[PDB]
Structure formats: C-alpha cells, structure tokens
Image (cartoon, coloured by chain):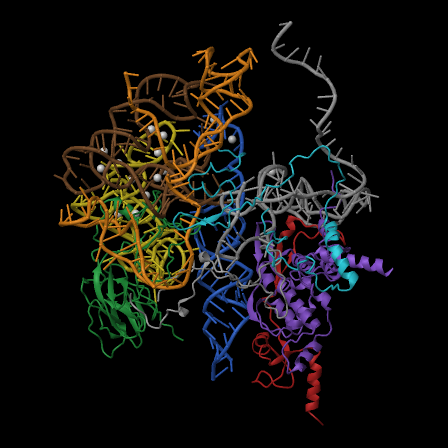
Chain colours: B red, C purple, D green, E cyan, F blue, G yellow, H orange, I brown
Amino acid sequence: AYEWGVRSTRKSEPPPLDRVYEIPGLEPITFAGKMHFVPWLARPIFPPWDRGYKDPRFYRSPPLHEHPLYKDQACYI
Amino acid sequence: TVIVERWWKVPLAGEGRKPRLHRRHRVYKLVEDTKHRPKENLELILTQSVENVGVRGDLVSVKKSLGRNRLLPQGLAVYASPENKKLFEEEKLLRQEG
Amino acid sequence: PLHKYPVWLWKRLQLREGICSRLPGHYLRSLEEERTPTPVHYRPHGAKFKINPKNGQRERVEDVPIPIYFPPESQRGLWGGEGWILGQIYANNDKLSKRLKKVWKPQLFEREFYSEILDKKFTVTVTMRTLDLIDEAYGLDFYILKASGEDLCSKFGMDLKRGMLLRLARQDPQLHPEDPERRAAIYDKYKEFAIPEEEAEWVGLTLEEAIEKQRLLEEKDPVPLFKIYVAELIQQLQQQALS
Amino acid sequence: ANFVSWKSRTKYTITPVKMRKSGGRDHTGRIRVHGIGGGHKQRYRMIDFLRFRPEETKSGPFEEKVIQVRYDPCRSADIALVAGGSRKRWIIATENMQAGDTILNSNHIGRMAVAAREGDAHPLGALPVGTLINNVESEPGRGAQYIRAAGTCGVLLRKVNGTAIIQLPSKRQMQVLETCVATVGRVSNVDHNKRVIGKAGRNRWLGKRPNSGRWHRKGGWAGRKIRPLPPMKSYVKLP
Amino acid sequence: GADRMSKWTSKRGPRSFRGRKGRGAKGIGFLTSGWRFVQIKEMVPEFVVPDLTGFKLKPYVSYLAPESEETPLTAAQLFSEAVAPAIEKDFKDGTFDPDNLEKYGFEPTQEGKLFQLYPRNFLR
RNA sequence: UUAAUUUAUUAAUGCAAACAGUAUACCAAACCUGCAUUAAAAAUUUCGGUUGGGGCG
RNA sequence: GCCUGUUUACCAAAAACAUCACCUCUAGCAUCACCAGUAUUAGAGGCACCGCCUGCCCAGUGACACAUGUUUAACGGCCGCG
RNA sequence: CCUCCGCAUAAGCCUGCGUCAGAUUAAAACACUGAACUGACAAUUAACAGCCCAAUAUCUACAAUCAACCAACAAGUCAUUA
RNA sequence: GCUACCUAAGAACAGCUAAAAGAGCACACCCGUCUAUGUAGCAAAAUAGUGGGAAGAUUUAUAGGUAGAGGCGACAAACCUA
RNA sequence: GCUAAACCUAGCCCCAAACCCACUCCACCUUACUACCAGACAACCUUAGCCAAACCAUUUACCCAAAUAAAGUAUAGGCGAUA
Ligand SMILES: [Mg+2]
Ligand SMILES: [Mg+2]
Ligand SMILES: [Mg+2]
Ligand SMILES: [Mg+2]
Ligand SMILES: [Mg+2]
Ligand SMILES: [Mg+2]
Ligand SMILES: [Mg+2]
Ligand SMILES: [Mg+2]
Ligand SMILES: [Mg+2]
Ligand SMILES: [Mg+2]
Ligand SMILES: [Mg+2]
Ligand SMILES: [Mg+2]
Ligand SMILES: [Mg+2]
Ligand SMILES: [Mg+2]
Ligand SMILES: [Mg+2]
C-alpha cells in the first residue's frame, strides 16, 4: 500500500539521550538549575506538565473513546 | 590502527620542553598496519562440554572470532587469567582422586 | 602596556579565582596532571640514545606524539587510543612529487558487550585494538577500571568507570536479594581498587559539569534574617541574665 | 532556504489539494533539473493506484460503479471517479469507460481462467494467455507502478508454477508473483502522440522552459546503439 | 540610504508593522476571532485615592522646624522596635517556645497571604 | 589538451580483517577500513634566445 | 531567417538564441525538486514546420557487446596519371 | 495660455513655505520676505487598515468569462459537521 | 529591493475591424531603429515623431530562495548595487 | 592694510610597578531598545597564501617553554636558495 505520509512533513523524532542515563545507580548532572538551555553537555528528560486551572482559551478536549455521548454504533446525520 | 612515522625528523626541542612542530612535519608515511597480518589464536578455558572444539577440563587455543561470538557471550569459556587457572587446576585435582 | 601573567596561565588563574577554587583537591590534581598517552600510531624508541649508521656517534632520540582528531562518535562509543589522522601523504612515496592530503579512518564493528559490575548489555561500535585490550585485560570491567583517563579517550568510558567505582564504594545491592553470594563474589573480585565515595563522584566529569555540581551542592536558599535576629536576641538576653 | 514540501496530508480525501510548483528547486535552492518553470496553475488529485482494497469490516469482493470521467492535468491520461459502497476513491480510467459502467475488484483465484471484461480487475492467476493488461504491480500489497500512462498496456506471455511473466511496453520481459492484482484493458486517452503542439504557448502553459542555447559538440554517445534485449529482471525472492 | 542613528518608533514600518510596536502601553485584555478587544476589569490599574477632608498637613514645611541627624532605617532597628518587646515580655514570664514563631509576624512561606514581598504581587 | 606531478571524490574491480552455514572442494549476501587500476573533476605551472620592429626564412 | 519574441542595461538589437515538425542515447522506477510521475513517461543532445529526399564508411577517437563485431541524424572523410 | 495633470490609496526620513522676535552677519544663483534659517508657541483624537481565531475526529469532483443558448482547454481564485 | 530564474496570493489592457486566432490599427502601458540638440549637459545615458507589441512567450505592487574552486543564462563569457 | 601669519592643552608612544572591570527603576533576542502561552535540531575538523630559489611543481624563521657561549656544530634540504 502506498502511504500518504511524508517523513519530511511529519514531526521528526527526538534525538536519542546521552550515555549517562544508561548507567544504573548514577544521577546525571544536567542544566535543570540554571534555567536556560546549554551548549555544555546539557539535555535531560522533563516530566509532563499540566495546568491546574482550566482556561477556555487553552482547553483540550478528551479523546472520543470516553465521551459521555459516545456509543458503539455510528449514526448518519 | 595505522602506524605512521614523521618526516623531516623532529629537531628535538629540549628534553622537558614541548616539541615545536612545523607544517612540514604533517607529512607522514605508511609503514605497517594492524591488518594484513597473520592473526594469532587466544587461549580460552571452557566450562562445559561442547562439540569437537573443546571439552570440560583442559584448555584449547581457539580463534578470536569464535571466542568473541559463541564462547564468551554465552558463558561457555573464560579468559586465560592467572587467577581462575588456580581454582580450575584445584577442581581438576580434586576431581581426579588417587 | 604589558600583561602581568602570560597568556597560557589564564586558565590556572581562573581555576585559582573563586568559584573554580572551591573544587576538591583530588579533582584539581587529576585535572592538572596531564600525562602523555600510550604510543598507538607510532613505534616508540627503545632507549633514550640511539646509534645511527653512517657515523659512529650516539645521539639522543625522542618519541613525539601524532596530533589525532577525536570526533563525537569517539566520545559516544568506546574507542581505543586511535582516531582520525589529518596528515599529508606524498605521491609515489617520494618528496620530489606532489604533497597530497590523506585522512585515515579506523574500522568500526557494532558489537555487544556485557558488564558484570552493572549487569546490563550495551551496543558499542567497538574497533579492533579495544577488543585486543579487553582480551588482554581479561574482561571489560578490568579494562575499564585499570586504564586511566588518558587511555579511554571517551566520555562513556569515564562514565562507566565512575559508575563502577560508585557501585563498589557505596556497597549498593547490584542484583537483588535471595542470593547475596554472587554479589559478595563480585565485590571480592574487584577489591584491588575501592576508591572512597567522596573521591569517586568526581571521576570523569568535565569542567562545566563540575562547576554545575559544585553550584548545586552550594545552592542553599537564603535563610531569613528573622531567625538570626531572634537567635542573637535570645543569646544577648541569656548573657545579660545569667551574669 | 525554507523549502517545505506541499505533500502534507496523511489521509486520503476527495477534494483536490492545491500543489506548489518547483521549477527545479530542491532544498538548497539551486537549479538542478533544467527545463521546468513557469506554467499554468494546477490542482493535485489524490489518485489511488492500488486497485483491490477491502473497506472497513470487509474482506470479500465488492462491486463498483463508474460515475463521471474527468481529466487530470498532472498526467497524460484522464482520470475517472468511481463510486462504490460508502466511499469514493479516484482510480485510473481505462479505454471505453463511460458513465453507468460496472466493474469488479475480485481477489479469489479460481481453478481455470476468467473471461473478464476490459474494466474489471482480477489477479494474474485467473487471466487467459494473451490478454492486454495494464497497471501491473511488483509485490503483493504494494501498489500499481508499471504501465500507468495513456494507452500503455501489457500482454501476458506464459506461466510456470507461481510466477507470471508480463511483457512490458519496452519489449522487455519481467516476471512477478501470481498473487498480484492487475487491471485488464488499455488506458483511455489514446492517440496522445498525434497531439500537435502548434506553438510554444502550449509548452509555456504546461510549464516547460525552452532548452539551452549553447552549441554542444556531440561526443561518442550520439550514435545509434543497436543493442540486444536485456535479460528479464526477477522480483521473486528465492531463499 | 535610510536612517540608522534614530530609534525604531511606530512611524517607519508599513501597514503590517503599525500595531505590534506601540509606545509601551500596558495591555488590559486580549483579542478574539471577530477583530474585537476583550477588556478585563481586573487588569486595569485601579487608583485608590483616600479622603482628604480632615487632613492638616501642608506640602511645604516651615523654616522654623529644627533639623536632625540622618540615618537609614535598617531592618535591625525595626526588629528591635517591634518584635523585641513582645519577645522579652513572653520570655520574662516563662512561655516562649522557639518551635512556633508565627505569632510575631514571621511567615515561613509567601504563598499563604496575598501581598507577598519577594515575588512582589502588588504593583506600587 | 594527446605539455608536466597525482586520483585527493564516485561506480566497477583483485587482495586482507569482520560475520554464518557447508561433505580433502565451492559459495563471499546488507553495512565500515587500507592498498593498485579505468571515464568526470581537478590542488599548481610554464609557453627559450638573435631576428636592421615581431612570426614566417 | 518558418512566424510572435528575445539577446550585447551604457557605441553592434542583427542572418545572433529560442520556438512547434524530426532524429540519437539512457532508465524496470515510491517519497526533500526530478515525480507525490511510470518505456504513448522522464532525463541528456543536433537541425528546426508544411513539399522532394538524407547515397557510403569503424583504417583513426569514443560508446555498446568483450562472440574481433555494431554504431556515424556520434567525432570526420567521398582520387591522380597516361 | 497649458492641462501628458490633479485628488486619494500603496512604499518612504518624519514636522520639513502657520504665528512671534532677529531680519546687523549668515543659505534666495538679485529683491520683497521665504519651499536652501535661529529659538519659543502646537497641530494629527477613528468609525480608515492592522493588532486576530480553544480543542478532539470527520466533510468539501459538476469553474470564472452578465452565465441563461452554444462552444471549449492552459482543467481552474473563495463552502462544513458531532 | 536594478538586473537572470523560480514560488503564493492580486492588479492592468479605451475604441474599430472582432474570420475561430500566442489576428491588425490604435489610449494608457513594455522596449528603444533613425534624425536634431549636450558630452564638466536636465541626466556618471535626456528630450518629439518616424518605431515593434499592446487578450498574452505581456507588464507590475507584496513576500521568500539560488553568490564567486560560484549563482543564473530563450548562450550576449550577458547580468550578480553606476 | 585687507586678505591672513606665531601665541599651549586635551594629551599622544614605550618602560618599572600593579594582575583591570562590569544592575539607580523599567526595556534588550520577535520588527533588540516589543510585559504576558504547547516540539524541545543548533560548537567539538591539517589554515591558506605571497615572496625567495632570477620560473616553479620539493623547500621558505612566524610554531608563544626568559639571557649567553657552544653555534650558525652535527644535521634536514630539486644536498640549494635556506632551516
Ligand atoms: Mg529540444
Ligand atoms: Mg542549440
Ligand atoms: Mg624574442
Ligand atoms: Mg626581421
Ligand atoms: Mg526572425
Ligand atoms: Mg547596446
Ligand atoms: Mg534589454
Ligand atoms: Mg541599439
Ligand atoms: Mg537559429
Ligand atoms: Mg548524411
Ligand atoms: Mg531572459
Ligand atoms: Mg495579437
Ligand atoms: Mg499591434
Ligand atoms: Mg557565441
Ligand atoms: Mg620566486
């Protein structure tokens, strides 16, 4: 099957992490304290972040697999 | 690793000083490389019984390819170090009693 | 005007300034050591004096290093004492021709190893000299722990060395309980080193990483002056009351 | 050089997507292919070259129905939207295909051959020897790539045991697996070589700049080469 | 050539530049999808002006006022003037506890009350 | 350019290391390294002397 | 010189370069232009419509087969004396 | 007497023939005083164009040319749903 | 940002003959074959017509890309800020 | 005698010594001199060339470790101008 997705147009994959996270029992020394992106070996892993207060201008809707009006069969409007 | 020698010869900038180099010293010349050489076989002591390449007991000098592929990663052979040979010969002497 | 210190002492001056002066002594000594590596791309001379032909007079000979280049692929993987040689090669091995430029490249074999101290397999594009050194050192952990910083020429090697040193110093459970005999045997096999904990954490770190670690250790949010004020006040009242 | 491709649509649709011309400009910006530039604006149509394809919760054969035959400026032949089921996809039209036609997209290979028409499609394992076919594939479930222009067609030669040698329009033989779906008949929009240009305005509208004016001396490759037929290339992977 | 020594104001760019530059005015809202401005009443600086009825203090001082020495008002003086008497009073009797100090005005964090000092939530 | 040093970068080659089966023999797949060759580029250069003005004689 | 047009901005605006017709060679093919195309296609070259036609050659060069050969609308050439 | 001009929009430094005193000197190709000036006084107030769009999945093949006859080819400049 | 090429969204072309047209004359517009004026001129390339096109291989407002061991080239060794 | 001639001080160069500095509030990485919103990609690389040898293809101090004699000695160098 001829796919319609171009690799140059889609989102590129992030580069792999450095060789410091593959060491069991060794914490990395990144730049999470200086609060600016560095040239010196500095690229950690940031945890996800969400907003505690909902904003109408920045509200994301949940997927379709858990809507209260979602059913198994599909209708035709 | 490619072993090369320096041309024009170093002028010897003292014995405790940094050797001063010139742009002409960049020219090298290939003399001998690690490849294109008849390889040698390493000694590995096996710990289990295999086919006709080894046996549990003595040692046999096998090739480097086989040792690095299907002997060391699978835990079928140990290096010929002066530390494990002592316990190996001790176990061999205790196995073959009088 | 003129300068007070030469141009090749500003690094030492900055190290002896303030923020870089709070570093421990062992780290500063390991950084200022600067030792020549082992000859790889050239055969070193036997004795310091060599008798050359054509004339029966002894002359002192010296072995000069080869300026090799270290790409980031060398720092990511585990390479030996080789690299890229950006030199020049004549035509038909004669100086009466043309001086061309030739850059040699080492051979890369993507293999897979198994560290016993860390108990985890890693995919490293290993060469041939590194495999030979591993076979001569009887394992990978011995090759990593015995070779100094001037022999690995890679950041992953120094990271592995520091991790093994921390694992051997902190006595942290490597595998898991229910079988401590294997961990005891592993710790007894690597007992001829045992670098203390206060010195193993500063092995292989660069200058920027060391400065960042020293700043994180010396962070400390500013304590409010109210506590110091009430402490001085209670001390003064106790001193004036107990007398 | 902020050169981004216009092929930014990972879902098949029916609305013609606007395309951007290039004129021989890659990602760097230098002209690498001469003779392209300046033409009439065109709209791209998502043409589905894979003939047999099951719908949602489907598996067996399905019927189709030709609606209307239009024209595609991106190629020489004309396209025709064929509706069927609960979806509509653009496919390549064939010769003698008008409105109100019925075509079949089957896949079950039978014991004997099938005397199909010049509109429906069937695998090569059920077609008689000596049938004008077109839009032949190379791998099972890959898509039609060979013989897709205007009027081009291929004829089946012989069969062995699991392969099917197809005679290409370049007089060259080429075999393929038996489980490959290929259309039957010839492509529409015939007599394309007889299309008289007339003036350079047509070439400028199509988007083709004139050739270089430099007088190049012909080397040794300008002579006629009377060469034999190259051997048949095989795509069947053998262990 | 064009000018270079002069600063970049709002009368130099074309139709696409007049708007996003401005003169440093503080925004009190945002925009929507219909070219409208949604002004929020909680973003405009509300000027709090007290009553000036019974206030007997002129903006100019008389020359008959005697002068005095000048000294900065550091935190130590305010501390010794405010918290020191209360601490001495509660310690001279026998009820001081170094575990809790929130009853003297000290706050361990600034996220509890509204008017925070270090992040400065108030304008001026 | 068929005037001079050379292929520094390709595709084809032969050799050496790297993998895996194979009854005293053959097969050398995809991707790295060095040596020598073939078509394109090229890193550089010069174009001697008298010639009752210079070339031709 | 097929035509319209364009070229030496600032001494030549032309018979000069291009244009449809014709001929030669190369390519069995999916993601960044070529091409979201399939040997009625694409790229590399010579003249440049419609009418009469393109007769010969691999000794020399290159290209293709390595079968001693094919190619000239590939580089070029088609006598003298009595 | 000319109007082969002007008024607006688009691009462009932003105060560049309004008043006052100096007008002895200084720039008008000479003068009055002012499109080649020194200091003070303040013009232009938006409704004009911008400053823009909360997401998850899905939908959009029958041109324009008075678009109603006809006729095409260079196959085309505009829309939504839960 | 002048000029060679490409890309996305726009604008321009009275009137007559309109043979269906990369048709003709001809406004505005694109370029400049010749005469006359000056070469320290209005101008480090101007002034009127005689000029070719002006429904398309035409011109233009905006934004972006192709630069020297190169860019581009309907090939002038033409252009890349006099 | 009109045009016009001279009147010293901002300091300017190198030594010895000394190691020299960087927020009063706001604005400064987008159209810097812009208060306010959802793909995190951005360094780690033989310098070259002119001249000289009457050309030029090998070669030509410049390389950042305190003086001097050794010594311009052995050496390298189309064994030559040179180093
Ligand atoms: Mg052509
Ligand atoms: Mg030509
Ligand atoms: Mg002469
Ligand atoms: Mg003469
Ligand atoms: Mg003509
Ligand atoms: Mg001219
Ligand atoms: Mg012109
Ligand atoms: Mg002219
Ligand atoms: Mg011509
Ligand atoms: Mg002929
Ligand atoms: Mg042109
Ligand atoms: Mg016309
Ligand atoms: Mg006309
Ligand atoms: Mg010419
Ligand atoms: Mg010279």
In the drawing, does residue D163 fall left or right of residue C112?
A: left
Q: Nearer the viewer, residue B16 or E45?
A: E45
Q: Nearer the viewer, residue F10 or A1?
A: A1
The answer to whether any part of residue C51 appears in the image is no
Q: Position of residue F5 (x, y in %)?
A: 54, 49
Q: Quadrant of the N terminus of chain C?
A: top right
**Measured along the vertical axis of the image, is residue B49 above or below residue H1?**
below
The answer to whether any part of residue D120 appears in the image is yes
Residue visible at 69% across and 69% down? C165
**Measured along the vertical axis of the image, is residue C237 above or below residue F28?**
above
Ligand 2 is found in the corner quadrant, namely top left
Q: Quadrant of residue A37?
A: bottom right
Q: Kindly give the residue lying farthest to the front in the view shown.
A: E54
In the drawing, does residue F18 fall left or right of residue G29?
A: right
Q: Quadrant of the C terminus of chain C?
A: bottom right
Q: Position of residue A21 (x, y in %)?
A: 59, 66
In the drawing, does residue E35 fall left or right of residue C173?
A: left
Q: Quadrant of residue B38?
A: bottom right
Q: Nearer the viewer, residue C225 or I55?
A: C225
Q: Quadrant of residue H55?
A: bottom left
Q: Position of residue D128 (x, y in %)?
A: 22, 73
